[PDB]
Amino acid sequence: LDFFTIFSKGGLVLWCFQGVSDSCTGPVNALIRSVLLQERGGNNSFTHEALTLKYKLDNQFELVFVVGFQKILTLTYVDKLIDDVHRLFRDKYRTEIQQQSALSLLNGTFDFQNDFLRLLREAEESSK
Amino acid sequence: SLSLEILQIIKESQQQHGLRHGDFQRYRGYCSRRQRRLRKTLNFKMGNRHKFTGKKVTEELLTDNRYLLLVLMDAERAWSYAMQLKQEANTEPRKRFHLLSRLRKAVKHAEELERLCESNRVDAKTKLEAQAYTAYLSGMLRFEHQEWKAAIEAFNKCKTIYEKLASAFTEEQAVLYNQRVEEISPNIRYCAYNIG
RNA sequence: GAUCGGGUGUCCGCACUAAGUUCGGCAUCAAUAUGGUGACCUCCCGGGAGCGGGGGACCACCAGGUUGCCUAAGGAGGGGUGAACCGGCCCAGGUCGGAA
C-alpha cells in the first residue's frame, strides 16, 4: 500500500500515514466527484491519472475508507485488508462513531497507526 | 544526415489514436493500417501472390528516412497487443503465455532497429533514442517475466539516457522527457521494492 | 480613399502523401507432466467355447498446468458434413458360440 485515508462524510480526515511517498493534494477529490455525480458503482473503478484508487462506504456511521496503490497490478488482498480494518474500526472506535455530534469526534484521538501497521505486515506476509 | 524523433512520433500518435482514454485495440488497428499504407506507398511488398519472402531493410535502403518507421510500427503493434492482453488476462490465465510470446518478440524488432541505427547515414540523436526505447522495452519484458535484477538495470540505463537528453535540451523541449521518466519512475521503485 | 499594387478557392480526365469505407485469395506451430478415447504390437493368470482379469511398447485426437533456439501468425474459439460398407459408441431384426 502506498496511500490510505480514513475521513468522515463531513470532510474531515481522521487518520492517515501518507508520508513522503504520496501527498493528498487532489487524489480523493476526483473520487468524491465521481461518487457524487457519476455514481460509479463499478467495484472500485476510476483510477484518476497515475495511481489506482479504491473506496469503501459505511452508511452506519457515515464513513469512507480510501486506499490508493500504484497503477501497476496488485493482488486481491487489498479488499480483505479494507474489510478487516473497517471491522476493527467499528469494533474498537464504536463509542466515537456512534455519536452523531462531531464534537466527540473532534475531542477523541485515535492511535490506530500500530494496529494498521501490523495488519499491513500480515497482508504483506500473506502476499509474499 | 537524416534525423528521427521516435518518442515524439509515438507520443503524438498514441494520444490521437485512442490511447488518450486507454483503448489498445484501436491503436493496434491503426498501427496495422499505417504499416500497410507505408509499405504500399514505399513499394516494399515482402511477398507476392502465392509466395512470401521476408526481407530485412539493409543499410542502403534507409536513405528515405521512412523504413525505420516500419520497424517502429511493428514494435508498437506488438507492444500494444501485449498491453491489451495484460488487461484481458485478469479473467483468462491462458493469455499470459501469448502476452509473453508477443513481448519476447517486440524486443527483437527493437534490437534490430537499434542495430540498424549504427550506420553513419543517420545522425547521432536517433541512436540514443533507439537505445533508450530498446532498454525500455527490455525492462518492461523482464519486469513482466518477474526478473527484477535485469529490469532495474535496464530502467536505470533508460532513465540515464532520458535525463541526459532532457538536460541537453531546453526546458520547453524537455517536458516530454520529464513526463516519460516520471511515468517509469514508479516501475523503478516497485522493481527495487520487490526484492525487499 | 481616384487610378494603383498583388498575394489565397470556387475550374481541372492532373500527381503524391496522412487518416477511414468496401470486396476477394493464401496460410493459421511445437516440446513437456497427468488423465481419457480409437487402431496396431507384446507379456501374462483362469476356462470344454463365446470369454473374464491384470501389465506394457508405439501412433492419431480432445479437456487442460507450467513452456519455447517457433514464425509475417500459429486462439487451448465456434459450426457443419461425417461419407460406399473405412472413427467408434449404444446397436433392432437377423447371424455364430452355449441346454440356458
Image (spheres, coloured by chain):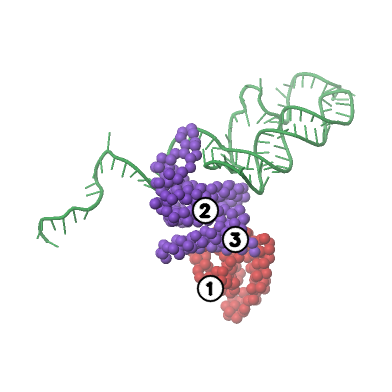
**Vertical arrangement, residue C26 with respect to residue A94, above or below:** above
Q: Is residue C52 left or right of residue A105?
A: right
What chain is colored purple? B
Q: Is circle 2 on the same chain as circle 3?
A: yes
- Element assignment for label 3: helix
Q: Is residue B168 left or right of residue C31?
A: left
What chain is colored green? C
Q: Amino acid at mark 1?
A: Gly
Residue C69 or residue C95, whichever sits in front: C69
**How much space separates mark 1 and mark 2, taking CA atoms?**
47 Å
Res B178 seen here:
yes
When asked about the image quadrant of residue A7, the answer is bottom right
Residue C3 position in % (x across, y down)? 10, 56
- Element assignment for label 1: loop
Residue depicted at 63% across the width and 76% down the height: A110
- Name the chain letter of the residue that bears numbered label 2: B
Q: Is circle 3 on the same chain as circle 1?
A: no
Q: Residue furthest front?
A: B120
When asked about the image quadrant of residue A16, the answer is bottom right
Q: Nearer the viewer, mark 2 or mark 3?
A: 2
Residue B164 or residue A51, whichever sits in front: B164
- Name the chain letter of the residue that bears numbered label 1: A
| CB atoms of marks 3 and 1 within 8 Å | no
**Vertical arrangement, residue C13 with respect to residue B194, above or below:** above
Of callouts 2 and 3, which one flags the residue occurring earlier in the amino acid sequence?
Answer: 2
Q: Amino acid at mark 2?
A: Thr
**Which residue lies under the disc numbered 1?**
A11
| CB atoms of marks 2 and 3 within 8 Å | no
Residue B192 position in % (x across, y down)? 60, 62
**In the drawing, what numbered circle is on residue B134?**
2
Res B78 seen here:
no
**Which residue lies under the disc numbered 3?**
B191
